[PDB]
Structures are given as structure tokens and as C-alpha cells.
Amino acid sequence: SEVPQVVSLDPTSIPIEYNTPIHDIKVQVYDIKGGCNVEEGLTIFLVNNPGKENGPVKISSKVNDKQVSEFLKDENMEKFNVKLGTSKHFYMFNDNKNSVAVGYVGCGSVADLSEADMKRVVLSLVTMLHDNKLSKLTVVFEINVDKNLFRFFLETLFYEYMTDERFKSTDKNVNMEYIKHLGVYINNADTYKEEVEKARVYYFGTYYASQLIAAPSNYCNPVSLSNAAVELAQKLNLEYKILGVKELEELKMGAYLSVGKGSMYPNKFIHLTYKSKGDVKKKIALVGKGITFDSGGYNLKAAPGSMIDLMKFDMSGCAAVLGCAYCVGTLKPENVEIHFLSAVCENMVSKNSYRPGDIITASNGKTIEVGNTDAEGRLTLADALVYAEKLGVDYIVDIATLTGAMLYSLGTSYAGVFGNNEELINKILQSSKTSNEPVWWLPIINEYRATLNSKYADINQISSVKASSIVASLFLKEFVQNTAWAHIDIAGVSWNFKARKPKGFGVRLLTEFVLND
Amino acid sequence: ASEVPQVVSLDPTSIPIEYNTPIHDIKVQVYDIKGGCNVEEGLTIFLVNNPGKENGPVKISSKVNDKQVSEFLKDENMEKFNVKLGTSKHFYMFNDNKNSVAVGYVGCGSVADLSEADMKRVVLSLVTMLHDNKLSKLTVVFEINVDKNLFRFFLETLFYEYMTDERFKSNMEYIKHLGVYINNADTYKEEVEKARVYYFGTYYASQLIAAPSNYCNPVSLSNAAVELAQKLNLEYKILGVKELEELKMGAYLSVGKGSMYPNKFIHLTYKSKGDVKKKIALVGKGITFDSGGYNLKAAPGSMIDLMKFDMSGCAAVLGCAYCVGTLKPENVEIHFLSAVCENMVSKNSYRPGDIITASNGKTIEVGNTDAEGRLTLADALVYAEKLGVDYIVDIATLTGAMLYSLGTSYAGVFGNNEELINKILQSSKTSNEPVWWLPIINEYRATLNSKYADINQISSSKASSIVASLFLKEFVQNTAWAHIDIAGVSWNFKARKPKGFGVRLLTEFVLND
Amino acid sequence: ASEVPQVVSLDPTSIPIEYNTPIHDIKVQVYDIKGGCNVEEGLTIFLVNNPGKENGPVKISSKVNDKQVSEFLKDENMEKFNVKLGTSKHFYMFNDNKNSVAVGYVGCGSVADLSEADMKRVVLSLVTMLHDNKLSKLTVVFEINVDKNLFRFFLETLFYEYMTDERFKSTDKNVNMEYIKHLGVYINNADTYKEEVEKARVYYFGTYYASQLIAAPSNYCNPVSLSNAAVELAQKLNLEYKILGVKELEELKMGAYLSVGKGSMYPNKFIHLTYKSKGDVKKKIALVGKGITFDSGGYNLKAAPGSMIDLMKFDMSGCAAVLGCAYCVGTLKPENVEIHFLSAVCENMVSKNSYRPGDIITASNGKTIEVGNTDAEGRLTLADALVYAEKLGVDYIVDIATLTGAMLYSLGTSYAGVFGNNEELINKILQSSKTSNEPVWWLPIINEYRATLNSKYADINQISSSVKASSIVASLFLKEFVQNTAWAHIDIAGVSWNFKARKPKGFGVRLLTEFVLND
Ligand SMILES: CC(C)(C)C(=O)N[C@@H](C(=O)NO)c1ccc(Br)cc1
Ligand SMILES: CC(C)(C)C(=O)N[C@@H](C(=O)NO)c1ccc(Br)cc1
Ligand SMILES: CC(C)(C)C(=O)N[C@@H](C(=O)NO)c1ccc(Br)cc1
Ligand SMILES: [Zn+2]
Ligand SMILES: [Zn+2]
Ligand SMILES: [Zn+2]
Ligand SMILES: [Zn+2]
Ligand SMILES: [Zn+2]
Ligand SMILES: [Zn+2]
């Protein structure tokens, strides 16, 4: 529990903001058929023109202001078009002789917005929120949107609006000022009002994961990460258990323990549990890869393009699980039992580190020949999956930044899912649709299994086939004997390279999976 | 036919092709296993397994009508051998008639349902025994469960691996008879001659791919396509440089600028005798050699010595043309297309940064001369859509990223039409040529926005297989279109030979449509 | 013995060693071919060739004491088969007593004198017949010409390849493993070859023992656990032993050897085994083996492509070969000779305590060395070991080491290179290469390259810069640490590991033993 230090200036805990400015925003949803009030702050219309690409802007909503309504006549709006991402600011006086701000955001010509298009709309909307000291924002929906995408709008809006300044000191933004009120005019308002607070939950779950990922490896260490998981569990009244080295040794987790041998931080196994009141119909284990830093070990990440400066995100799998734990622990689903697991450690270079060629024994008795110390994720997951299966669960779902090969297969937008059970895989895909975190199904090709046959050990850690994502899945499959299991590789989608910040991918995906099961 | 240019007189002027293979001379009969096996001649191999008992002992269940062989096949003798997948034993002995015979087995593991990859290992083990056999007859006894498709796949694979290409060469003898004992023999009899057609179609493609680039050039390959067309009574048309210029195929012509061999566009056609209800275009990548261009393949692992394989798309299409022209499906019209050229470094060569104009009017900024396949296919796809077909399916060794995504066993399929995707996947199942559906992610489309041209050839930077699909997608306007990337599965690296991947897949596609 | 340090309790504290192998339970019987062949239980294999006739027909010349089998193996029936090297066939038939017997052959090509490489292909072909078949007896009939050494090499290679290492198997132990209990050998002039049998069984395990160590991973085989194995072996053979720790090494001022191991969690251990004859000693020999239990390369990390860092447990081979030699010598017990088995064991790791590139260190003989590359750690350890060896007052010093990767580019994977300062000793090793059938080639120490080892500040450079012939330069470095004794250096970096078979060869054991025996 006590974080070790090299010097006194070393941080002993992860700075975490629980009360974010977003939580201070009062959100009201009105019915658009009742008319719009344009009084204070900025009012933004989400408009489109179906079939007519770059078509003119037309405000259909009734505005309860004679002056504003005249400004928004079709003749005045014709000069502007609805191209996706386009935004404009209007300045005018209303009926009560007050200066007001109005605008719009282009939503293209397609009636059904993609999750990427809606992301483009929101990102465009946030630009109007930045560098402007507004106290209230009003969004008028003049497009058709369902409950999931409406919730997705709010989640994305909240996430992008917030700015992480935990590690700023002399460069804190002197102009950062968040809105205090949020008004939303939309079709059939009563059906959408419930999505508001669910969005706020999904938001913080994602951003909590984001805070964990963005934190550097000197702040976020195997100990400090475990201490944070406890504090989270304590706040959510979740049962929690942190396994130390001695307990791991008794469980004979040689693969997981080997990875952390070269670290100054002791290995920590995170075990959070949520149990519903009443009869449990489904028991689920969510496993997150929690490598606080990945140097690669003696197979050091020194080659060009190894992205070692980023490798602090190698616990994004764990972060997604903890973020999910917040959401599950907050919304409190029924008839489910969830186990949040993470074999947390750090992959470093030392006299104590494990070497390429070392043969280690997993907690299930299988001997493993290490061919590459930078393939440490599958080793920690190996023991983690064995632990998970011993819990006697119905579903085992792991999430990990496992292979860099994902950048060559699916890229930076779609995560890959592997599994031994098509039913569970379909459940993940359905969750991907409703959570709007895109996932593509990839195969576990059994023909490659022969390349993992070790001459001396029971199995090789790596192949010597270049299809790393599939070969890694073959390895993990060997540690789930008779349980439905799925493996989500998020190595390519976890980090937003364009925005230079985490996505917190997985929180919404896993939560929708647990809730809609 | 056109005259192939030469640098020296010793330069070959034709691709050697073997049409009459020893496989075509093998008489194949299928017997029902319920009647017991007759072991009087040649080599007899039992395909056995042991379900639930991993690496379990061998036990021959079938009754054999020979006392000498029956004593050999008794359980006490066979239990000394195990059923580990691929494991083989065979013994020489005299039968009841004092004739010299050979009897043995191939282990088929402990799984009741064999994959196509498992069947490959079984066949390879079987072929090893054959390449060491002088006997005239091989008898295969199925004491395992296989359906019609897997049995035909067994025959296709056996025939293919058995055959050895010695065209460029300067022990054993091939068998004359093949006996097969299997449950429901009458049901599998129909698969025999279909397998033999799928055989040569795959092997013909293999012959073209294996043929080096000094033998297989744009002109000689087009000549081979013509000769094949004449044998199959197919309508054919070979477009030359002057006509390609008239059709304004700038993207295609730019790739072949640096070659000593003129660009040649292959157009074969199969038309049904009855009313035509479906028109299909099959498009093959036809780079006889890919040096990479001025973006030379110089980096380690760029595999420049294998770059004769860069035609595999063309070979697969031409191989399908054989199967289609032989089996002669009804109510369908199929167009076999291939923009064939050579990718070389010269003063006349296309350069990185060059802006070229495709036959559809789109200007393309070349960011990498080694991404030439999508360029040649671009004009090919524009040609294909002009034919007014229902389905367009292109197959190509397009991106090396496939080796990092699906590997060397599974090919990737991309497309703009899900129903067409499903038809390819269904064809993958029946042909036993494994293919996996990969997404065309539209969020990556923006990375192709050129500052000066209409579109970029390549991306700034990662998912190159998806980016390449996004590029090809820009050249099919209103037709169901699918794209098969076989760069990873085309070459059998372990065996040092082609697979002929795609031939059976494409044929099953047009047959079961 | 020392206690092996651990990071976690699950870290192994000893090298698993199998002394009693199934090969040791095999009874070997040798018969003269002129007496006729008996074909009964198990598998009976004929070794046939056809001199001058490439892929010629099979012809069994030996008399078979069975009417049925003799008819089966008549020339008319065997014509259909050929003698192509490595080709093998299985025969099934009933003998005179109405019993079913298994007979077969292995093709030995068309050359009358088989090379060592050809013989291994024959044996490997023979082993395939032993695998996946539950035989109780193997019978080998020699219808080819072999000398006493080649006959012994056959048995050694057969025993070695037949054996399977399952020390590190757990849930993937081969359930079908069942070794033969009897081995029959039919050969002309049998009594002359019978003496080679037990020599082969001793040479086999000596090779396999070294192989067991080499194949053993670095977390199992560390400087402490490896030295412990040497003690255990010496005790079983009643060899004198001394294991020097850091304190003793510090007192002997072995700065070069100690500097390599600075960055390791495992303390340095210097292995010193001694065999003395019970009679007057006429010859004194020191055998030095490189003993790096793992070579990460140091701060000159093995990060370049093809640097094979996952293999770097194999950096043991020299020490393992010397220990394997100690077994053969301790078992066969040669006369009038005293052998010193030496190895400076340590581990080259990256740490805060690690030695740096540029560091100047002092060897035990006073020479100062400027470190230009931490991955050239072998010659540094050998430097102190060669000084130690020469202080023993011996007649010959022979070192064996996986020293330079340049050997893969020079001699390849089959032939080891030998360097030296004494021509007569070099020729003795070459003769040992002949009799042991472990291929060794003589490579030159080119003195013109010595000037590139001239350090600006230290007495001598660890490595060169302008040569790129690392193997020769490494020898030039080592020569500077042997003042006035015949010394030879065997670089086995290329031949130690069998890449195709993914296993060690145990190269050096038979070579060094033949060297000690015939001297
Ligand atoms: C093949 C290899 C380079 C070893 C790899 O995929 N490494 C993982 C990794 O660090 N596993 O622990 C990896 C994962 C994500 C990214 Br981005 C890069 C590399
Ligand atoms: C990104 C780049 C390395 C240029 C590539 O995808 N090359 C293709 C190619 O040359 N297509 O024409 C490629 C295709 C197959 C193989 Br194997 C390697 C490279
Ligand atoms: C010149 C250099 C490439 C540094 C070399 O010879 N290295 C040794 C070595 O690491 N000695 O300690 C070496 C030895 C064996 C093999 Br395989 C590769 C490199
Ligand atoms: Zn890693
Ligand atoms: Zn990692
Ligand atoms: Zn190319
Ligand atoms: Zn190409
Ligand atoms: Zn080294
Ligand atoms: Zn070394």
C-alpha cells in the first residue's frame, strides 16, 4: 500500500479529480415542439439538409422570440450551408433588448449520422465552447437522433469539453471557464431525459480511465494504481481485494510474477467485485491488462517507431475495467455478478528482470518458454485468465493493449476482438454498436498453433508467423480450458495520436455489455 | 500473339506450360467402406484417428479381404503406432497371393471434425509416402468423417501436392490408379472429376506464378492467356499500348513505363449458350515482376526475390477461366480481366510524386511507386464497370500488411456490398480456401485527400490494407464490388512454391451463384 | 554449495539434471556378421550402400539364419528399392518359427567411405524409425565399411538423437515415449569394435550432459546453480574441486572477469575441477570454458536484428563442453596425466552496477584494458582464466568458447575454428577432430592486426575498430594473456547450437576428451 521512492520528490499517489466541472453543469431537456427560448449564453442549432450536399441552412424550430425568429428567417440563413463540421456565430438582440449569441453546426446531408460524424459535430461544437467565456449553452436538435446516439452526443461533449490540468503548474490555462447550465431542445423530450444522467456516468467512467492512462509511469505505478482501485471501490461500496507478492507466490503465478521481477514496485493483483441484490443470473469477469510502463524488458523498445515514450498507456486495459467498475458500481445493474480483475506490474530492465529464454510456470501448471520479454502482456494475462476461470464465471472478457500489429490490421479506429465462443463475441459486437466504441471480429487461426510448440517447455510465448494479434490470442486461449472467453485488443485505438490524449476506450463498451446482458 | 522482346538471344520467348499432367492419367474409383477393403495391389493407407484419446493408439476397424494383411492390421500390432496428426508408417509385405504390397496409415489426430488445414497435413504425410513409391496403385481408406466438400478438397490437395513442376529442371513413378474406401461412396463419386478440374485450374495458376519473370513477362503471359482461350473456345481480346492510350488508362500505363515489355490488358470472356441472367467481372493483379520502382524494395524482408508472385491475382483469374470454360456453367456471363505489366527502374520510369490520370478522369498523386497494384487495378475496375456487370470481384497480392493482420493462411476480403461479401464467404467455405471479412473504415478516407491531385495513392500513415481498399473503392461508382487481398496467402513459404490461392474460391463463387 | 538468490520464491534454485538416462538401461550386444543374422523381436535394420551406383538397388549380402527371411531379402525382391542416402523402408514378414518380425534398411549412398556428416543423416534416418514405434529391441546390421572411430560415432549420435529432453515439460509430456531395452549390432570383425561400445556410452552422456546444461534456461542455469552442478559432478566422479567466490577473486585481482559480472544479481563463481592419475604425472593440461549463463550484451545491448538474444543461454557451451569432458575423463580415467577443468562463470546484465563502455579495468596479470564494447565480455572473462591457467604450471592450455558471431560468417554451423600460439598443439587438436568426428578448422592469428588493439590510455583495447575480423582480433587479445605456455583457442559460436533441431549439440566434449586421452 505504501509507494516506494528513489528520491523524496517522487510522487506517492495518482492525482485524481473526482469532482469535475462537468458535474457542476445543470442539464435541462425541453420538448422542441414547445418552442425555444433564446435568452442567455450561446444557442446552437444542429441542422442538416438530406439529399442536398452542402445544402442551405433552414431553421425549422419555432423560436419564442420575435426578434430572434426574424434573424433566423430562411432568407437570412441561405448564405450558410450545412456541410458536416461547419459552424457559424451570430450576434443579435432579442425581444427584451438583450444581446444574445446564436449559431449552428452542420450535420451533413446523410439522415443517419455515423459515430465518427457525430464525433465531428461535437468536436466542432467544442471549438465554439473554447476561447469563449459563456455561462450557458443551449443545443437545439433539428436532426433525428435515437436514445443511444443522443447519449453518445452528451458523453462525447462532456469528454472533449473537459481539459486535464492535473500536471500543469505554471502553465494552467488562465482562460478556462466552464459553462454552468445546459439546455437541450429535442423531439420527444420525455424519452431522452433519462439518457442525461446515464451519459454523465458513462462520461466520468471514461474520463476516470483517461485520468489513469494520461498519468505518467512515475505517478501511476503498480502500487499507486492498486491504491486508486481500492479508493474507488471504497467509494462505490464494492468488495475489493489486492493480492501481494506472497499470495501470488502461493497461487504459483510464475508468468505474472516474472514480468514484475525487474521492477522496484511490488506486483499487485486488483480484484474488485460487484454483486447485485437478489438472484444472480450472470457471473462475469472483466480482465484488464495493467502494465504501468512497458520498456520491453531486455528486448528493449529501442527500434525506430516503438513508441516507448507513450508506453505508459500499457495499463489502458486495466483503466477501462476500473472505469467500467465505476459505471457498474454507480448504475447498479440487477441479476449480475461482476469481477474486475487486473494483474498489475511494470516491465523494466534490471539485474532482477526475467531474460529471453527463461522458462516460467503459469498458475495452471503449463511451462512457458519466453522468446521475447516485450510480449509480457500475454504472460500477465495468462495467470489472470486462470485466476478468472477459478472464480467460476459464465463469461471471461479481457481487454488489452496487447499487440502493435493492430495498427497494421484495423488501424486507430477499430478494436479487434478474438474469442472461443461466438455467442459471447456477438454480445461484445452488440455492445460495440450501442456504446459506439467500434470493434471488429478477428479470427483465431488454429493452423498457427504449431508455431507455439516449444522444444523444451510446454508452449512458446511467441512464434518463430508474423500475425502477432492472432498468435497472441492462440496463447491466451491455452489458458481458458472450458469457459466462454473473449479477447479485445485495443493497442491501436487506445491512444488518440491526433489529440495527444487517451480515449479511455472500453469503459462504455464493457458497461453496455454488463448492463444489456 | 505478340513478339516478346529480348535483350540477348538466350532470353526465353515463351512460358513453358504442361497441360497433360500425370494426374490426368490416374484412374480413380470410389468404393463403399461397408463392404470391406480389398488389398491386392499397390499401397494401402488407412486414415485413422482416436477421439478423446490424444496421441492415442492406432486401431484398424475395417475388414480387409486378405489373411496376410489382416494379421498385420491386428490391434496388438497397430497399438504400437499412434494417431498424432501427420504421423505415418508403412510396411512392405506379401499378401495371400504372394504379391508384394505396401500397407500403412496416416494419423488424423483426435478431433472428429478435421479442418482443411488438418487435411493438408494428412495429405502431405500421404504424398511423402508417394514420392518414395514405385507402385502403380494407391488405396486410401477413410476411417474418419469427411463431407463432400472436404473429400473433394482432399482430392484437389492430394493431386496438387503430388505433382512436381520440372519445367525448369534439366526415386518414384506416378500411380495409375487411386482407390478410395469411404462411407456413401456413390455420393462422393461426383466429386472426383470436379476435383480433377479444380486441380489443374489451381496447378495452371501455380505454373504461371512459379514461372520466373524472365520467362513470364507481360507479353508472354498475355500470349499464354490467348492460347488457353483458344483451347477452351473462349472469346478473347488483348489490348495493346496504342489502344490503352485511346482508352486513356494513364494510371495503368504509368506503372509499365519503365519496362522493356509493353503493357498488355487481358480480356477473356465466357458466355452461356442459354439466356444470360448474371454478368460477373473477375479482375486479377498482373505485375509479372515488382522491383518496387524508384521506391525500390531494398529494406530487409521486402522479399524482392519472390516478386514474380506479384501476378498471382492474374493467375487465379486465368485458372478460374479454365475451370469455368471446362465445367461450363449456365445462365452466366463471366469476364476475366487483367492489366498486365512489369514494375521496373529506368529512365522511362514513373516517379514518386508524379500525378497521373486514370481512365475515369480522376487525377492520382503517386506517393509510393511500390504501391503500383492499386494503380493498375484502378483502370481495370473502371474497365470492368463499363462492361455493365452485376458483380465485380478483384483479387490481388496488394498489401504486405496482410502478413501482419491475417498471416499466411487467411486472405482478406473488402467490399461495398454485404451480399457480395457473404457470397464470397460462402464460396470460401465450399472451396476450403479460407477468407476473412475485413472492414473498409471510412474515417481513413480523409487521409487520401491530396493537396493538388484528386486523390492520394497512399496514406500519410498504417492500416494500409484498408487504405488500399478505400482507394480502389473510388473507382467503382455504382456496382457491387469485392476485393480479395492474397499477398500473405499466395506463396507457400515453407514449401517454396505457390498455392494457387483463389482459383477454387472464384470458381465456386460463379458456380453456386 | 552456495544458495541461489531469488527475486521471487518461484525462481528455480537448481538445474534439473538427468544422470540415469534410458540409454544407460540399454544392453548392447555385438555379433560377427559371418556368424549369420538372427531376426526376431523388435526392428532389424540393415545399413546398405551401392558403391559407384548412384541410387543403386538394395542388395543384402549378410547371411540370415532364417529360411523365410532370406527368401524375402533375396535380390529380386530388394531391387525395387534403392540406396539413396537417408532413404529407409519397413518390411513385415513371418519367420521360420511362424513369428512376425520387423525388418528394414537405411540407404547409405554410393560412397564407400562415409563422412561424419553423412553418418549423421543415416542415424537421423534411423531414429525416425525408432520414433512413434513402441519397439523393445533394435538390431543394426552393418553392410558398410566403418573404422573403429566411425563405428563409435554411430553409437554416440544414435544415443544422442534418440534421447529426448523433457526436464522442462509439465502438461505436454510425450505419453508415447518408450525406449528400447536392447541393441544388437552385427558387424565384421566384431571383437575389434566391442571395445568402442562403452566408450560411446560414456562419450554420449558427456555430450548429453553438456547439452542438458546448455539447453537449460538462464533462470535455471545461473552462475550459482551452474557451479553447484560442477561440484555435484566432481563429487560423483571423485574429482578435486574448488569454487572461488568474489572475495577470493578480489584477492587474486581478477578485474576483467569481475567487471563483467558486476551488473548481475548472481555472484561470480570460478569453477576449478582437477583430475589426477594415481601414477606418475607426465602431462598437465588446462581446459578453459567460457561460462556466461546469459549474455544480454551489457549496455551494448543485443538489440540489433538477428542478434539472437533469446538464444543467449547458449553462451555456456564452452563451460558445458569442459564439464562434459570432465565426466568422460573422470569415468574413463586416463593414465599419467593431470587435467584442470576451468571456467570463469558469470552473467552479463544491464544494471546501475553494470560496467560501462569506456571503462578501464585491470586484469590479474597487470595489463589494463579499455572496454569499447560490453558485448565482448567473453574475452575479458577468458583473460583472467588464461592467467589463472598459466599459473597452474601446465603443459597445454586449451580454451573453448562461443566467442564471436563472425564464426557464422567464416566457417558456418558445422566447423569450429581453432587458433593458437603453438603449431604442435594445434595439430594435436586437429587429430582429435578426426578421431572424435567433431569438425575443426585451423584459422590464423594475423599479427598485422595487433596494432589495432593499441589503446591511447590503457595497455590494450578490448576490441578493435578497423578490422571487422572479430574472431582473429579476439584471439590476438587472448594471446596477450598467455606468456610462455602452448595455448589454443576453439571458437564454437557457430557450431554449438543446432538451429534446425532447435537444440544444443554438446560440441567440444568428445573433441577435448579425445585430446586428453591420446596424449
Ligand atoms: C511484436 C511486439 C513488438 C513484441 C508487440 O506487439 N509488442 C506489444 C507489447 O508491448 N506487448 O506487451 C505492443 C503492444 C502495443 C504496441 Br502500440 C506496440 C507493441
Ligand atoms: C506498403 C508497401 C510495403 C509499399 C506495400 O504494401 N507493398 C505491397 C506492394 O508492393 N504492392 O504492389 C506489397 C505487397 C505484397 C508483399 Br508480400 C509486400 C508488399
Ligand atoms: C563482434 C560481436 C558482434 C560483438 C561479437 O562477436 N559478439 C559475440 C558476443 O556477444 N560475445 O560475448 C557474439 C558471440 C556469439 C554470437 Br551467436 C553473437 C555474438
Ligand atoms: Zn510489451
Ligand atoms: Zn505491453
Ligand atoms: Zn509493389
Ligand atoms: Zn505489387
Ligand atoms: Zn557478448
Ligand atoms: Zn558472450
Image (spheres, coloured by chain):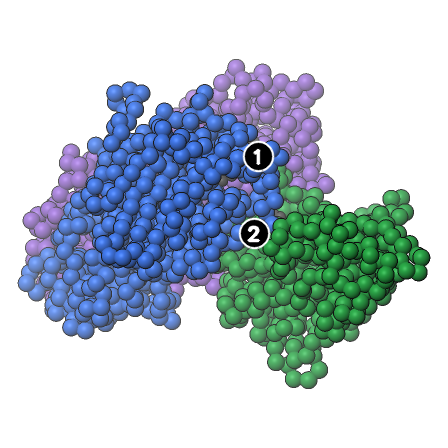
Chain colours: A green, B blue, C purple
Q: Amino acid at mark 2?
A: Ile
Q: Residues within 10 Å of mark 1 (few under 14, many from 20)?
A: some
Secondary structure of the residue carrying tag 2 is: loop
Q: Amino acid at mark 1?
A: Ala
Query: Which is nearer the eye, A254 or C204?
Result: A254
Q: Which chain letter goes with mark 2? A: B
Figure quadrant of residue C50: top left
Earlier-in-chain disc, 2 versus 1: 2
Q: Can you give x and y, in whole percent of width and height, for residue A183 in the image? A: 82, 64
Q: Quadrant of the N terminus of chain A?
A: bottom right
Q: Can you give x and y, in whole percent of width and height, for residue A23 in the image? A: 83, 64
Whether marks 2 and 1 lie on the same chain: yes
Left or right side of A159 for B223: left
Q: Label 1: which residue?
A: B453
Q: Can you give x and y, in whole percent of width and height, for residue C388 in the image? A: 59, 32
Secondary structure of the residue carrying tag 1 is: loop
Indicate which disc residue B441 carries: 2
Residue at position x 52%, y 59% in the image:
A441
Residue at position x 60%, y 64% in the image:
A433
Q: Is residue B127 visible?
A: no
- B491 in relation to B115, above or below: above
- A203 in relation to C362, above or below: below
Figure quadrant of residue C436: top left
Q: Residues within 10 Å of mark 2 (few under 14, many from 20)?
A: some
Q: Quadrant of the C terminus of chain A?
A: bottom right
Q: Is residue B348 visible?
A: yes
Indicate which disc residue B244 carries: none
